[PDB]
Image: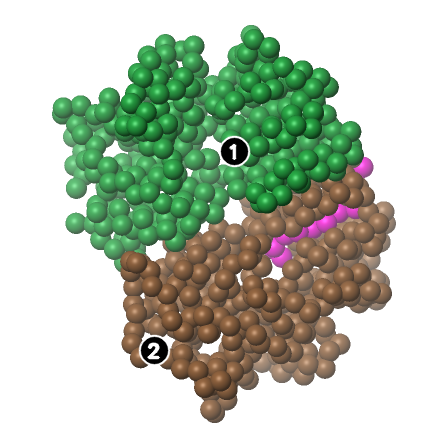
Chain colours: A brown, B green
Amino acid sequence: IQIGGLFPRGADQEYSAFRVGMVQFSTSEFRLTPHIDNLEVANSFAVTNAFCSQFSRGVYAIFGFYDKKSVNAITSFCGTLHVSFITPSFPTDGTHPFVIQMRPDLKGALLSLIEYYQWDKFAYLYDSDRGLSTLQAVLDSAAEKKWQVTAINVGNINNDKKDETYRSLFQDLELKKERRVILDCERDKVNDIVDQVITIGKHVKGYHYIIANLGFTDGDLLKIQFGGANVSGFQIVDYDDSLVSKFIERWSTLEEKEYPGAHTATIKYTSALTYDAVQVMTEAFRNLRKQRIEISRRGNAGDCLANPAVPWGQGVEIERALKQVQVEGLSGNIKFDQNGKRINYTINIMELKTNGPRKIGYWSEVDKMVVT
Amino acid sequence: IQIGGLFPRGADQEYSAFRVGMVQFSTSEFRLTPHIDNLEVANSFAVTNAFCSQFSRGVYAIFGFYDKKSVNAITSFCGTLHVSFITPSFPTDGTHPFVIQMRPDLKGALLSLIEYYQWDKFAYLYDSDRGLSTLQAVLDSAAEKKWQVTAINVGNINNDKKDETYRSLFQDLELKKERRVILDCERDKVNDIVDQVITIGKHVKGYHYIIANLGFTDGDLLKIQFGGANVSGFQIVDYDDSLVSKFIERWSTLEEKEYPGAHTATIKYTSALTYDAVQVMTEAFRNLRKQRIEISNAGDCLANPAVPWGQGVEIERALKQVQVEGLSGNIKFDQNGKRINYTINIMELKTNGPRKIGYWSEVDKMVVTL
């Protein structure tokens, strides 16, 4: 069963996690065979081309990553042609079809926590790249719950004055005597920022930071474990989980030059979801034999732009099979709604104490109350 | 010289403005011949297909429109393949190449005005559909100049509870006793917002509204000329201008069934820029003979590897170094296709009518009261 892979450049850990999943989840009676393409995922042209190529090859589904600058390109083609796209990238805001979204929604949990700490005046530092879905919720709810949010787009600082203007961003932000802050950026920025918070000595007592992403332990927490600032975040990989322990003991011992990014004690949530994604995909094709469904080409349709666009017949079966999969993985309960969004899922709430990161509770999609 | 046209559906006025420009700007020695495609511009699939169609036809440039949804699709293909795209849609935030952007940047002017009125607590009503480029500029600043902005995305209200929830959005917005307000919506959402403002009687004295777009007179401002509320906005078409008067006399008398959307006293700024766009293109191809530059089988846009059209950059250059006067005044571009050396009239709604109370220069950058 042929599938396509659209991996960003230097998505090493993720590709390794993907290959590991391939080995583990494929069997004798059943083997996925992926054609992998590596590309600049923010380039809509590159992405449209990568898609159209796989479409001629005759793939049945596509595992991939997309970016704010390329998401519409990919979803529009998937939706139009009935190719299902499975992805660990950010969930789409809209109810798009033929997109199975492995990443859970953080908007929900982040708002509950802001209330849990009973904040009502803070700062919000967002990266334009991530998608801006969350900026709005914080703003929408700051109207409702009357918060005084101080939003600043931080994604448009170039390496040139990286350290120079970050430092002077607190000569602009100390103005409102701002103490509680939320970080919503790609890991490279999050680190780049923390580094700067320390350098200027705003990691001391009196400051509280929330890391708006799903991998709290994913990066280097240590550098501020002892400044005296409060530091909170989210984690969808429970390393206390049996399933996850068994995984890491193999992962931590992989040939680091055969599996780049491996041979470590933690795994990035994106890499985790990439691996869980191989499980979901394999299971949905096993359920398509277990319903004696013929999803095979009897013929091949090769142009991405043929007009009129005629959707693949079996396309809708494959979308269904995927969305009605339920398994347990590195991210716990994997279960989808009609729109390919994740449900019945849990996010650990985390605090950075002096001994280390602590799971202080969880956020259920259902209960929805930070449970402690 | 062949060019492509990518028009949204029911972009009537704009297409008419386009055809008019075609007539007057083309000569004996020089004729642009457009292949026109009408499409759902928010559909990146549709838009990419259309682009690729024109690309095979062998067009030299493309005039068109794009949507927050579909802008990356377009710019990405244009950038990659070296086809130049001229457009009246919102300017791109980046420095994308091969995009000549006819619409000036409103971020600049809007911020100056907020200071001119010396506001520091207001509401900002934005439309998701337009793009959130401005939402940031306002918020980035609200940090800097310590404003207390109350932002609300209003683009995700469906026709069902249109009136129902707009009204109850001031049962949520009267909370902060909110009196100054910025509207950043399409004309359609703008007038809908305005009617509701009147229906509930918040168009009275004590309220001040700023209309964040380039067509202050473009819609019906009369409905609230006399409520007693302050109402300000922007205008890039100066109807007092000689060049524009000559235009409207013709425009206002066109066969309304031969030129839909015409036969009126005002013209929408998009239609204006559409028309100005025919001038800019025309000019740039005339300057390409006036430099004895040769440009002339095209191929598949999905050909791999992508090989850029050789003459492509020449055409991008010619376009970007064009300077003329049009319905929007001084048309002049920087290296990035963005507009420069331009002016925006500042406008207030008085009881006799809208009044040009000043201007905003890209250079002076004052709100330059007069």
The tag on residue A297 is 2
Q: Which residues are magenta?
A: A177-189
Q: Can you tell which of label 1 and label 2 is closer to the viewer?
A: 1
The N terminus of chain A lies in quadrant: bottom left
Label 2 is found on which chain of the structure?
A
Residue at x-position 67% and y-position 74%: A333
Amino acid type, residue under disc 1 in the picture? Asp
The C terminus of chain A lies in quadrant: bottom right
For residue A97, above or below residue A329: above
Q: State the residue lying farthest toward the bottom.
A: A28
Q: Quadrant of residue B181?
A: top right
- Image location (x, y in percent) of residue A274: 56, 71
Residue closer to the observer: A305 or A314: A314
Q: Where does label 1 land, which residue?
A: B188
Residue B307 visible in the snapshot: yes
Residue closer to the observer: A324 or A356: A324
Residue A178 within the segment the image draws in magenta:
yes
- Image location (x, y in percent) of residue A256: 56, 76
Q: State the residue lying farthest toward the left.
A: B29
Residue closer to the observer: B265 or A214: B265
Amino acid type, residue under disc 2 in the picture? Arg
Residue at x-position 18% and y-position 39%: B295
Residue B303 within the segment the image draws in magenta:
no
Residue A41 visible in the snapshot: no
Residue closer to the observer: A116 or B336: A116
Disc 1, SS:
helix
For residue B149, above or below residue A326: above
From the viewer's perspective, tell me whether residue B102 is left or right of residue B133.
left
Label 1 is found on which chain of the structure?
B
From the viewer's perspective, tell me whether residue A131 is left or right of residue A82.
right
Disc 2, SS:
loop
Label 2: how many Cα within 10 Å (few below 14, some 14–19, many 20+): few
